[PDB]
Amino acid sequence: PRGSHMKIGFLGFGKSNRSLLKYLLNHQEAKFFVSEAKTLDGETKKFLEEHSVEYEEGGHTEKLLDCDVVYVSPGIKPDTSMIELLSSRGVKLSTELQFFLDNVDPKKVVGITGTDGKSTATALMYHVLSGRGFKTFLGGNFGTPAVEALEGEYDYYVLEMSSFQLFWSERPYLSNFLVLNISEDHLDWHSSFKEYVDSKLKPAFLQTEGDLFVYNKHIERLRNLEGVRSRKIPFWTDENFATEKELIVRGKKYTLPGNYPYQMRENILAVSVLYMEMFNELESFLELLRDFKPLPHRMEYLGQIDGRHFYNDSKATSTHAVLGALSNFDKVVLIMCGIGKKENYSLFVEKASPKLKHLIMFGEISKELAPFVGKIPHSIVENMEEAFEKAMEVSEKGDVILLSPGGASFAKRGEHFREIFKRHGGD
Ligand SMILES: O=[P-]([O-])[O-]
Ligand SMILES: [Cl-]
Ligand SMILES: [Cl-]
Ligand SMILES: [Cl-]
Ligand SMILES: [N+]
Image (cartoon, rainbow, N blue to C red; front, side):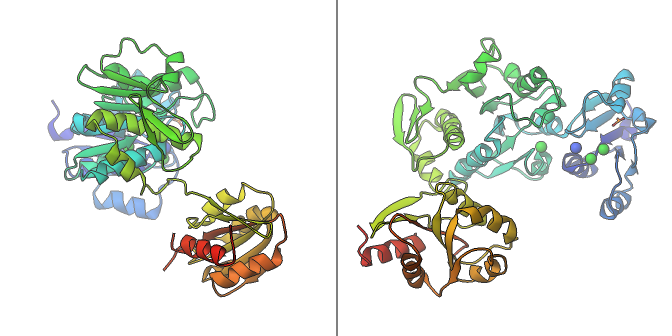
C-alpha cells in the first residue's frame, strides 16, 4: 500500500539488528530508523550516516510508533515501556531470527536449542555436515547472526537459537528441530520458567508430517508432545542413549573415541540421532567426530617409574586445557612447553598454583610464563629430555608427573614423551 515509504524500525542495535539492517539496506526499499537506549560509538554513527539511516540514541521515543514493522533485539524485555506502547498502537513486532526463517529455504535449516551444550552441539552439527562436503553456514545467538548467510547460497544453515530469539519470533518455522535439553537452572532468562519452556518449544508445534523433531525425552516431563505432527525421535530411550564409553543409536552400539563428560556425551548423542535420521549411517559421523576440535583429549596414564606416576596430556594446547588436566589431582609435577598463545598468564598461574608441586618449562612458552611464576618452585630447561629428567629429580615416590604443554607446536610430543618414558624403564 505504501511502496517505498515503508518505515522499518530497529529497537536496540546489537549484532542481530546490525546484521539485519545491513541485509535490508541492500534488499529493500524503505526508510530505516534505529533506536538505541545507550550511546552509539563513532564508527556506528558514521556507518548510519553513510547510508542515511536515521537514528536516535539515549532513549526510545515515540518516533518508533511511526514504523510499519519494528525488529526487536533479542535481549529487549517484554514488559518494557516501548514494547507496551508499540503493541498498544498495533505496530507489528518481529526479530532478526524470524526474518531469517521467513526468507531462507526451510528444508535447509537445522535449528538447535537447549539450556546446556548448545554451542558445542551446534558446532558439531556444522562440523559433520561440512565434512560430508556440504557448504554449510554456522551461526545464531552465540555467533554470526543468521541473516549474514542470506548473501549467496548454502546447502545447510545450522543455527543455535536462544529462548530470547524464539520469544520475539512470532512463528519460527523449522523443518529440522533439535532440542538438546531444557533445564531449570542456571538461566540467562528474565523470569518465568513456563515462558522459557514455551519459547524454546515453539518450532515443534509448527511442524508438519514431512518435518523432523529430535529431542531429549526428559522434556516430556514438561510438555505434552503427542500432538506434534513431524517424525519425532526422542533420545535417552531404550534405543538411543550413551554411557561413558558407548553410543547406542537405533539399538546399535558404537565405541566412542574417548570417555567424555556428560554434556559432551549428550551433544554427541543428540547430533547422532539426527545424522542417522538424515543419512541412515553413523560410520561417517564417527570418523568426522574424531577431528572435531572441542572434543576432549585423552589423558593417557603411562605407568610408573620408581614410584612416580606419569600422565600424558600431550594435546593440551592452551592455558584452559592445562587447567582441565590439573583438576584431576592435588599435587603434580607439571611440564609445559610449546608456543604460547597471546594471553595473560597471571589468571592462569594463580588458578594453577595450588596444584603445582613444581613447574617445568621449555620452548617459547617459558618466556611468557617466567614473569608470573616467581611464586612457585619452577625450572626452565631446553627440551623434553631435560624436562623428563628434571621431573624425576624434583619428584619422589608417590608423585604425579604430568605433561600438559599449554602451547602449540611448530601425539608428536606425546609420542616423544612416551618414548622417553620407555627408554628410562617405564613399565
Ligand atoms: O527500556 P524502555 O522501553 O523504558
Ligand atoms: Cl537499546
Ligand atoms: Cl543494544
Ligand atoms: Cl541469529
Ligand atoms: N540486546
